Image (cartoon, rainbow, N blue to C red):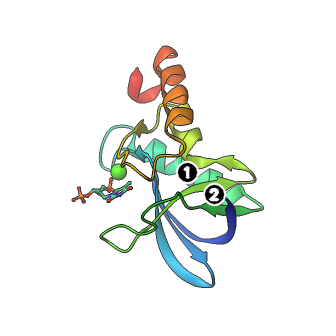
Amino acid sequence: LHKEPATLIKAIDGDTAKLMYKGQPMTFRLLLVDTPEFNEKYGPEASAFTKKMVENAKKIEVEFDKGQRTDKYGRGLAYIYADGKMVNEALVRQGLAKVAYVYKGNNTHEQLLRKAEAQAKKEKLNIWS
Ligand SMILES: Cc1cn([C@H]2C[C@H](OP(=O)(O)O)[C@@H](COP(=O)(O)O)O2)c(=O)[nH]c1=O
Ligand SMILES: [Ca+2]
């Protein structure tokens, strides 16, 4: 896989954000994770985590997997990096997202994220508390 440039347009919630990519606005959904919705437990905490991460970054990048690049809603499906740190992984490592929606052919970072989840679950962080 390879990282490509994008810029933040607006934070949305724990696992979506509006980015400019190839000069067009798109809503991206984070591959291989699920955050709570804003109205659910840990929802606001996930939204705040992702917001801080993407807003404070000097450089946002998107990394598509080998499969579908957009979902049925027209959302971009990617791994999002903030100054080189993967947001997807960070959320899971903090117990603010579960590994989820692991579809065949877009699952390159699955075992990275499952290792993060195991460590969050050992620490009883957040969703795992
Ligand atoms: C993360 C992801 C979600 N989706 C679809 C599956 C779910 O369909 P349904 O809307 O029918 O439940 C939805 C979950 O996204 P949200 O967690 O943002 O709701 O997005 C994909 O198709 N591919 C993906 O990689
Ligand atoms: Ca969600």
Is residue 35 left or right of 112 when viewed as pictured? left
| Amino acid type, callout 2 | Val
| Residue 26 higher or lower than 61, as above or below | below
Q: Is residue 38 visible to us here?
A: no
Verify CB contact (< 8 Å) between mark 1 and mark 2: yes
Q: Residue at x 49, y 39 (%)?
A: 110
Give x and y (percent) for residue 26: 49, 76
Q: Residue at x 52, y 16 (%)?
A: 123
Is residue 85 left or right of 70 when viewed as pictured? right
Is disc 1's CB within 8 Å of ligand 2? no
- 3D distance between C-alphas at marks 1 and 2: 6 Å
Q: Residue at x 62, y 52 (%)?
A: 52
Give x and y (percent) for residue 55: 65, 60
Q: Residue furthest top?
A: 122
Give x and y (percent) for residue 12: 46, 63
Decide: few, some or many residues near mark 1? Use Cα within 10 Å; few <14, some 14-19, many ≥20.
Answer: many
- The residue where tag 2 is placed is 54
Give x and y (percent) for residue 120: 51, 24
| Amino acid type, callout 1 | Thr
| Residue 42 higher or lower than 74, as above or below | above
Q: Is residue 75 visible to us here?
A: yes
- The label shown at residue 20 is none
Query: Which quarter of the image is occupied by the N terminus?
Result: bottom right
**Which quadrant of the structure image shows residue 8?**
bottom right
Q: Residue at x 63, y 81 (%)?
A: 22
Judged from the image, the secondary structure of the residue bearing numbered disc 1 is helix
| Residue 117 higher or lower than 83, as above or below | above
- The residue where tag 1 is placed is 50
